Length: 125
Length: 125
Length: 125
Length: 125
Ligand SMILES: O=C(CCCC[C@@H]1SC[C@@H]2NC(=O)N[C@@H]21)NCCCN(CCc1ccccn1)CCc1ccccn1
Ligand SMILES: O=C(CCCC[C@@H]1SC[C@@H]2NC(=O)N[C@@H]21)NCCCN(CCc1ccccn1)CCc1ccccn1
Ligand SMILES: O=C(CCCC[C@@H]1SC[C@@H]2NC(=O)N[C@@H]21)NCCCN(CCc1ccccn1)CCc1ccccn1
Ligand SMILES: O=C(CCCC[C@@H]1SC[C@@H]2NC(=O)N[C@@H]21)NCCCN(CCc1ccccn1)CCc1ccccn1
Ligand SMILES: [Cu+2]
Ligand SMILES: [Cu+2]
Ligand SMILES: [Cu+2]
Ligand SMILES: [Cu+2]
Ligand SMILES: [Cu+2]
Ligand SMILES: [Cu+2]
Ligand SMILES: [Cu+2]
Ligand SMILES: [Cu+2]
Ligand SMILES: [Cu+2]
Ligand SMILES: [Cu+2]
Ligand SMILES: [Cu+2]
Ligand SMILES: [Cu+2]
Image (cartoon, rainbow over all chains, first blue to last red; front, side):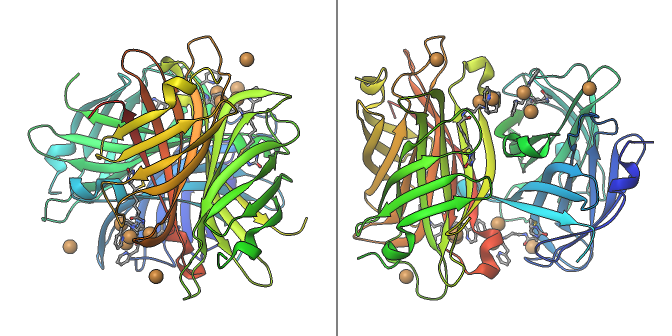
């Protein structure tokens, strides 16, 4: 089993009120759904990612990342977000991320194609 | 089938000489391997991602993203990179990305946990 | 005078314990010193930036940015950070930023030259 | 004088056709104007920044950064861009940057306040 397979698997919430439901596999896989509280989004979207299944034991966090393409049966916002970050275990477990949201654009608009931000996920709220 | 399922599936190379081997599924899935020409990496790593399987038809690119956790049977660099970008079809097909590489860190080093950069992938070289 | 010239001018502290001392000019100038609580830094460094001296009146924040080159009379870490963000006035005034720290590198190391993060500055602590 | 004071001072052009006019001071100051070929911009905008006036001599680039607030006598786009990067001297001198563009937003829109991209500046074109 991955060191934090148990710690990562479950439901997570970020500061925007979005919901991140993920299953961590023993091999390093992340699978689940994402529901955004903001933007051109409704209901759940497929996500997939990877995490370090054998992290350092020196108190470092666990690196991970995942992607959502913002197309589902209800909407298509022609964009994708990737979250890159680390899982920090303990009493107040957290997944601390920065993210890149890229929209499909024409080449003349490519310079404004990508948003960057940061989301913190907790097990509560 | 996804509009660019055929266009995305295959082998891609970036400006660093890294090799991105991907299969685009009809549902929006990305699966494959990544081989980095630089950094604490050797041989192939598992990747997974998502792409917009029904992009706009107005000449916009196709949004996509994917993740590599830098653990395989040879090495574990306790880090993960996510690439967020868009596929641009045509004679000179390109995948234009920006990426976030997060290392597992202690909390005292979390401020220096994340690199950002940009990779351009072409079908040749 | 700039709408938030008075609001921005003064001493600010971020979540790392760093100290941001700035004077906002009527023309949009930012001048001051930065003292980082972390990294290859000691004492104060010169900073300069710009802010929107006539922001929207619809409740939006005030865009601003500034740069520190990490050379002073004590140390030279051959790097520069730029903070890009917005000032949010009111009872709990905040400057919410994301930043890019670029080190001078050889071309072979340019892919790992740039860190990205996010700092929140408050008037207290 | 700053090692690359002479190398940096002058007119630079990026891949979008924007024009970056800068004077590097002996102390590490950057002063000049920026004219963007794209976006909500017309004519020249004030910029200010900092650079490492005593870079490493091992072939590394010279770290630097600068800010433009997008207000001038013609327009106010209530936003600011910071470019963070390094100057690389030689026959084909380059300033390689990544940038963060933050718009003033309401707090409910703060999650989509910041664009990220990358500009390469050359002495010609
Ligand atoms: O909303 C979406 C999908 C939802 C994205 C939710 C984000 S993921 C990061 C964050 N953490 C989270 O939990 N939730 C948010 N994808 C298109 C994102 C278009 N813009 C903003 C929204 C919008 C809605 C309607 C019309 C226009 N926009 C991006 C802003 C932009 C940038 C550049 C040029 C033009 N517009
Ligand atoms: O190399 C790795 C895995 C390979 C990553 C390859 C990158 S993905 C983006 C890009 N596109 C590509 O095709 N290839 C590169 N993961 C740890 C990344 C540690 N640092 C740099 C390398 C290193 C090797 C040995 C010892 C120390 N570092 C990141 C730099 C850093 C940042 C903050 C604090 C300390 N160090
Ligand atoms: O510390 C500095 C200057 C201090 C920077 C402080 C940052 S500004 C953003 C943030 N908000 C804040 O208030 N404070 C921090 N500039 C070189 C930054 C080298 N690395 C990390 C530190 C270090 C100290 C000694 C030896 C090696 N590093 C960056 C990590 C890295 C990235 C890629 C390859 C290798 N290393
Ligand atoms: O254009 C500007 C100022 C010009 C900025 C030029 C950029 S600096 C980085 C790059 N290198 C360069 O040489 N040139 C470009 N500042 C507002 C930037 C609003 N959006 C895009 C333009 C626009 C024009 C009219 C109406 C709406 N937008 C940013 C996209 C966005 C993001 C999030 C939510 C909504 N919109
Ligand atoms: Cu180890
Ligand atoms: Cu968009
Ligand atoms: Cu806009
Ligand atoms: Cu559509
Ligand atoms: Cu690292
Ligand atoms: Cu370092
Ligand atoms: Cu206005
Ligand atoms: Cu560095
Ligand atoms: Cu490293
Ligand atoms: Cu030195
Ligand atoms: Cu904007
Ligand atoms: Cu939008």
